[PDB]
Each structure stands twice: as C-alpha cells, then as structure tokens.
Amino acid sequence: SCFLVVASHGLSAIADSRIEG
Amino acid sequence: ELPRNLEVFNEACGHVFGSSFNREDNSVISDAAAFLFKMHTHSLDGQEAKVLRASEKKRERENAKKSRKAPEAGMRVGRSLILTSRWTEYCATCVPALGSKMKVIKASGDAAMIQMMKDHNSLLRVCVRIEVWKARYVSLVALDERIQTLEDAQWFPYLSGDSYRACPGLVGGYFAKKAAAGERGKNYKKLNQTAIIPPPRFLIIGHRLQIGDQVTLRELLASIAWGLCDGVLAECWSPSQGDGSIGVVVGLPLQATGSCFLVVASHGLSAIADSRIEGTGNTNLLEECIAIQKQDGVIKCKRSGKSLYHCLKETAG
Amino acid sequence: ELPRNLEVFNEACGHVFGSSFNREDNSVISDAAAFLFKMHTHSLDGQEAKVLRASEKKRERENAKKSRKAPEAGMRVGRSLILTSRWTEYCATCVPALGSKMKVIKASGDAAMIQMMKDHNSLLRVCVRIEVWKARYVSLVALDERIQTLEDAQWFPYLSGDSYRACPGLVGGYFAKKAAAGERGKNYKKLNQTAIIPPPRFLIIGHRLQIGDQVTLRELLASIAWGLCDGVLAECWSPSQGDGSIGVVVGLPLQATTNLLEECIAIQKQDGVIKCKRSGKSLYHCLKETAG
DNA sequence: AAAAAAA
DNA sequence: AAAAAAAA
C-alpha cells in the first residue's frame, strides 16, 4: 500500500502517516 | 438553457449513443466522454494515421490503426453504451480533419467550419474535465502503482498529451512535468491538483457544485480531491436520513488553489521558504487545520493526518 | 509647473484619449500607460514589424501584426478609455521611427528630433514605472503562475524586455535574471523589488508619497511592496473614520532600496523611526485571511 | 538626476 | 472554480 498524504488546501505533505510523531 | 460547451457535448453523446446513453450515471458519462475524446483525437481504428514527425516505431502503430477496421454499429462501449448506426456520419461530419488548426479555418472564413472547430475544442475540454474527474474517482479506491513518493504524487493525474493540451491547469503527468521544467511563459498554467470539478452528471447539466447537493461521498471526494489527499476533506459530507448511499454536501474546502507560503526577504528581513514549517521548531503537522466553508460560516477543521484512500478503506471494513 | 517627464505623459494621454482619460483612477491611468507603452514600442496592430533578426515564428507574428488592421477612433482600450481621431497624428509625429537610436539623432543636430527622442524615452520610463506599480498591485491578491519558490520569487515583477530596458532597477523577470546571471558592467543596476513607486494618480502629477495622504491599503502596499512581502508592512496604513476602503499613510519603511520571527522592520513615522515586529506571513496570505 | 542601451 | 493562441 501507500501511506503518503500530498499537500492540499494549506496542509503540509506527509512522507508517511505512520512515522508522524 | 445550456452553454455552448454542454450543449455540444449533449448533442454529440446523443448522436453517437442513441438512447443507450444514461444522463444520470457518472460511469456511463465517463465512458461516453472517453469514447468521444478518442474519436475527436483520431485514436480510434480506421482514422488518419499520425505521421507528421512520428518515429518509425510510432508510424508502425499508426499504420496498424489505419489499416484496422473501424468500430461497427452496435458495438459495446464500456458497460452500458451501444454505438448507433449513425455514429459514422457524426464522426465524418463533426470531427475536424487531422491537423486542422483554428488559424487556417478562420482564414478560410467559413462560419460553419469555425463553429465546428469551436465545438470540437469545447468538447475536448469537457471530455478532459470528465477524464480528470474519473481519474480522481478511480484513485479514491485504487492506488496508482506509479505513485510511490511525494515527487511522483506531485504530478497526478497522469493523462495523455491531448488531455494536457485541452486542460493544462488540471492535467498533470509527463507533459505537466515537462512544462514545469521547461521555460515558463506568460501562458504557463500550474497544475491545480485539487481544483473543484463537478461530477459528470452535474458537469453536463451545467449545475455548479455547491452546498446541499445530493451526492455520494466517493463522488464528492473525487470532485474536491483525490485518493492521497488528506482525509479531513470527508468532513465536507454528511449522510442523509436513513444512511443509504447518497448524502448531502455540508460545505466545501477553502484554499482549493493558489496557496503560497513564501515570504521574500525585504526591508532587512530574512526570507522564509514555508510559513507553516518555520514556526520555532514545533513541526507538528497534525495540528494543521483546513478552512471548510459551510452554509452557516467558515470553520477550521483539524487535519486527520491520514490519506483519503486509507480513510475510505478503513470505513469500508 | 510639472517636470517635463510628467508633462510629456499628460500631453500624450490627452492627445490619444480625449476626455475619456480620467486622471484620478489608478486602473484607468495604468491602462493608458500600457497602451502608450505598447504604442511607443511598436507593438500595436499596423505598426512596423520587428523583423531585424526575428525567427520564422516571430517573423510571421510580426508580419501578421503589421497586416492586421490598426486601432481606429472609438476603440475601447480597457474599460473607460476611448481612442480619439488625433491618435494617428500623435503616433505619426511623436513615436520615433522603428530602430531609431539617440546617437544618430544627436549627431544629426535636429532639435525637433532630439526633443522627440528625449520625450519618447522619458515617456517609456514613466509608463514602465506605472507598469511595475500595477504589477505589484495585481500581485497583492493574485500571484504569478511562475512564482513557486524563493528562487522564482526573487525576480518579481516578470515584465517584458522593453520594460527592463527602460527601468532596469525596478523591472525583474527573465532579462533581470540574464543580467544578474552573467557578466556585469559598471553601468549595471540591481533590482529593487521594494523601491517606492507613488500610485499612478500621484505619479502623473509629481506628488511624492508621504505620511498623511489619503490612500487605500492595497494602494499603499503596492506602492511600497508586493504580494509576497511580509505582512507587517500593513502597519504603514491606517483606516480613517468609518474606513470606507480609504485610509491614510502613517509611515514608510526604511531600507526599501524564535529569533527569525523576532526580526523587526524600521518604519519612519511623523515622530521618528520605530521598530515593528514582523508578522511572518506574506501580504498575500494576510489579505486572504483578513478578507472575511 | 544627467549619460549609455533581444527567448 | 470568458475568450483568443497552441507534441516523449
């Protein structure tokens, strides 16, 4: 699968949702 | 009643598909628009071969296409679209000959031919908008294998060159990458990856997407975002009474386009490459918010931090 | 008693636009300046063709422009400007012939031709100053497509080649990039993205922007900065009684020509210089957020 | 401020 | 989120 979250509507891109912390 | 673009599209689809063209199914409209885009781009069998500056390998494919028999009447297209016996007449009459350019037609001075080319261009734009919407819709539940890193995701949707030429500001891919890399003129248009595109059943009717529309979650999301956009956008939807399948729109995202967070160095100040990240060291992205404009007013909603595709997958389990 | 620079511009605007030229509207003055600049650069339909070293496509474009019908009296240029019957005579007598060079004019010794060339150059400078101001004003609410990073934002405004040739110290873009990214001479001008340009309604009358004159927030911001400058510059303006989209200038920044957000700018007020803490958000973002 | 001088 | 230009 893919855990990316592209930057949109003023939000910052995330290279991996899980690693965030 | 309807603009020139939508009237042209309705006329074309009706002429080509008889009564088999359902005007209230997004999948059927998308399939019809794809077939029409192929027809008007001379990608179907039996149409003019593209040889102007083609390489021998491309010339092989073009000659094979030209030699191949054209689609026959009654042929099944997609799922529930059937070609009529009069589709050949429409293809011969309403499709500009290969290599046609608006300047030559204007120089000729034929009003009928000018209107024909204008209709062709408007149809191309409408079909490409529907193509981008269908690309987002597919991406909502089907990750593209090509997209593996944010650099690849930056150029969605990966549509052909004709799609880019029709809608440079909505279509991404190889040609958008080339245009961004290459020299940028006054006509350069940046890829608006989350521009609002009404569902095809709305786009052909000319109804602009707004608050209160009876739409499904997947189609609304494909309208306002795509698979890898954040899941907080799902807040722009609300199930109707009794749940069912179709809900209602409670709001729309703000800052859909034209978001710049640069602060150039001026008056002795130091430049900032990104206002959001600058902060002081607290790079907590989960605290970010999106401004959703609702009927009552604009509200700031905390980001979910999870892709729309993943949110939909989790809620479907 | 205005300077010749402004007198020439006013005379040209009058001759070419009749009474339709309103000297109190920034948009009207900007449109008139743009039309005059494209007239004096030989860019209007029916004018001479730039075919000295044009490529095939450029050769064809210039030939089509020459063959195309020239503007006629009554044409609508913008929103509130209508060409008069005198515009042909003005374009014939005041616009120097294509390719003319000041050296040859001075060598010939013709006083009339020398004056015409000097007036043409002064008019070009005035029109380009107005063009830069209008570019800032536009960018206050709608950023250029070419501005994606700081490297791109460093070359605002993206104006044409003639604009740069006229005011190299104010105009940016491709030609400013080329000049900066190349061998530089003694007569080389550095781009000043924040050089103070009075609003056109003030520029064409010689009034120097100063504390205490009635202006609009967008007007002042376009005068002293552009869209991507820090929002603290908004402190240079103050709304009047009832606002009404019209206020007054309370200061003008200096050096126009944790710690990162603690940087301050210097503002010259009626009393003296004061240090104002930066906002951290560009003027574009601040205007978007404060719009409602 | 005077001088100089297109993808 | 109008119109005129205009292929690896």
Image: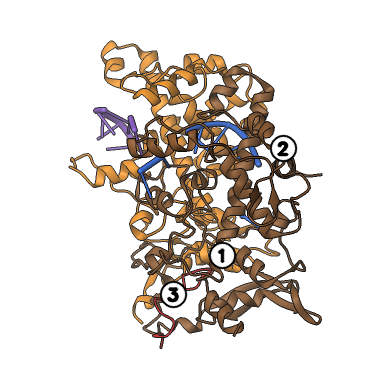
Chain colours: A red, B brown, C orange, D purple, E blue
* Horizontal and vertical percent position of residue A10: 51, 70
Residue B138 bears which disc, if any?
1
Q: Hey, what amino acid is under mark 2? A: Ser
Residue at 23% x, 47% y is C181
Residue at 43% x, 71% y is B275
The C terminus of chain B sits in image quarter: bottom right
Residue B44 bears which disc, if any?
none
Asked if residue C153 lies left or right of residue B29, the reply is: left
Asked if residue B251 lies left or right of residue C208, the reply is: right
Secondary structure of the residue carrying numbered label 2: loop
Residue at 32% x, 19% y is C52
Q: What is the distance, in whole Å, between disc 1 and disc 3 at their CAs?
A: 17 Å
The residue identified by callout 3 is A4
Q: Which comes before the other along the chain, label 1 or label 2?
A: 2
Q: Hey, what amino acid is under mark 1? A: Val
Secondary structure of the residue carrying numbered label 3: loop
Which of labels 1 and 2 is toward the front? 2
Q: Which chain does the residue under circle 2 lie in?
A: B
User: Image height check: is B122 above or below B31?
Assistant: above
Q: Nearer the viewer, residue B225 or C102?
A: B225
The residue identified by callout 2 is B85
User: Image height check: is B88 above or below C256?
Assistant: above
Q: What is the distance, in whole Å, between disc 3 and disc 2 at their CAs?
A: 48 Å
Instruction: Tell me whether marks 3 and 2 sit on the same chain.
Output: no
**Label 3: few (<14), some or many (≥20) within 10 Å?**
many
Q: Which chain does the residue under circle 3 lie in?
A: A
Residue at 60% x, 80% y is B301
Q: Nearer the viewer, residue C45 or B120?
A: B120
* Horizontal and vertical percent position of residue C206: 49, 40
